[PDB]
Length: 615
Ligand SMILES: Nc1nc2c(ncn2[C@@H]2O[C@H](COP(=O)(O)OP(=O)(O)OP(=O)(O)O)[C@@H](O)[C@H]2O)c(=O)[nH]1
Ligand SMILES: O=C([O-])C(=O)[O-]
Ligand SMILES: [Mg+2]
Ligand SMILES: [Mn+2]
Image 1 (cartoon, rainbow, N blue to C red):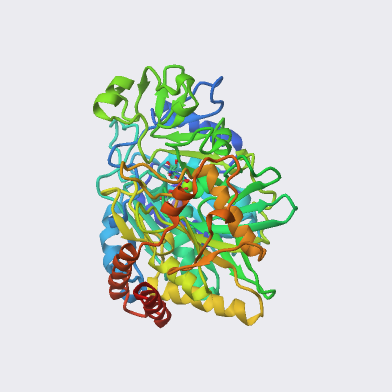
Image 2: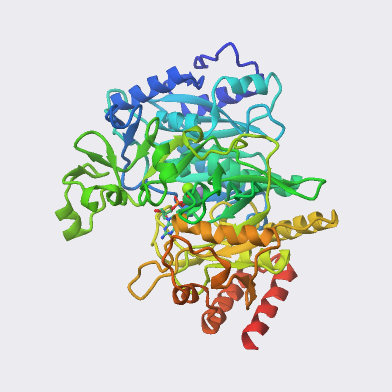
């Protein structure tokens, strides 16, 4: 067998044998075990610079930061190539792509057979959740991509410290990744190796994750979406907890009372910006802190509360639109020690993306840039062709500790108590600004039936309304109808303690006017919606009952510092009967597709909403 170069601190015989089997299959030239040190990170970055995958940015403008640009075919998630290969198809559900496990194993085995020829297999040990904590889970990702290795260092607890927790007998999540571009001897590589054929496959029975053909973070950082959502949602279903596509934030009012909220928005629909928003004018004495921006693990306790942890260690966030007005905490976070992917390159060796001109002199575009495809870019080219300097799904990768608004409990394994949930899709019509569910069941209905317009975070036509229950359409690890039942059973467990359940809200920042522009300013101004939620949590906020729940009146929000009239508020909060009749018919189509094991409570809630519309 090939020399594994197993470090002395790896004491797990079962792990070593698994690496041996995977090395025998993928046939890498060499094997390197990542220790996760800062020194190793710098060596791997220099190796990426040598390969042309990375360009080191200007140390004076963006210290210890790098820029990568990808193949145009490998810029986002590929949902059609993502599979849940459960033993039974009914345990994948209509929202997932299924294939018989042995049939998929026969499909992938020749693809991974020799996939790493001419490359180095990097062994990437990582922990999701704080190292050695009772809620943490350890995985090992084998990858032939140093880009994956350095991004995993930022996004997870990565390296040799994992093996101290694993010991001689600890179990791990087996993760295999390849760019699917084996190299012949003497063959020159490309700067972004990938394959037109891609597979992202999950075997829930064995917790195996197999990724082929893509270097993009969503497809290749196997601890993130593949384990911490798809695999972990299965485990939580069996063990009584949740893995959710949710940010976690803390918010403290001027009276010193602190609350925590978890919000599920679909990919590229506002989680990162909300999770670290800065309270605008009129909110002196308020503070917003970040626990996480993408994934939450949640379980109930005996005290009747729901406790949430963020299992990740960094942010892998959409770049375009970020500036000092929309998200200054993020701007400050990516000041250094950041990996940028598919943004533009300035003449001075800095990065640039659409939206940064809002902080520029005269709010003007840069005179010249090199776009994410390596082409010359000018304001004239952009004005005449609409060419974007940064890809719409371009990303930054940055450690959570770079965030000035990072909550002191961001890595507390005890978690934070969730006082309210928020669900919200990208909807140009229909959905009002904010609505409070009348009960846990009606809140689960809200989350189960939410829709959202597609974004550049996955390949395909953007701007199309689709059902995205709980913002988990691309990430649910089992049948979506059983997942609905899981949320309903959780609420009953909480209610049996005698506790008051967390409120559930539906939000929409994205209503559009006749010109296609957003009616609600959003970003920092979303604090005015969050503050009403806090009022409702304290029992001091008023609201009016309407078809889908309780909404604030104009006088129930704080408008200090924002010129937003009562007429504008009426536009984004009015319940339009015709629009919601059409929307409920789209709910019925969803329920038809999800008929198997669909909870009866959802059809009962729908019938109640239909009555309120026909009243
Ligand atoms: N109009 C408007 N745009 C927003 C708002 N919040 C975020 N955006 C924009 O929407 C895009 C997505 O924002 P993010 O906060 O990164 O979305 P996300 O949910 O974190 O996306 P993922 O990381 O893929 O899960 C960015 O271009 C933002 O500039 C908002 O409140 N109003
Ligand atoms: O990468 C992400 O956060 C996504 O696609 O949801
Ligand atoms: Mg995000
Ligand atoms: Mn996400």
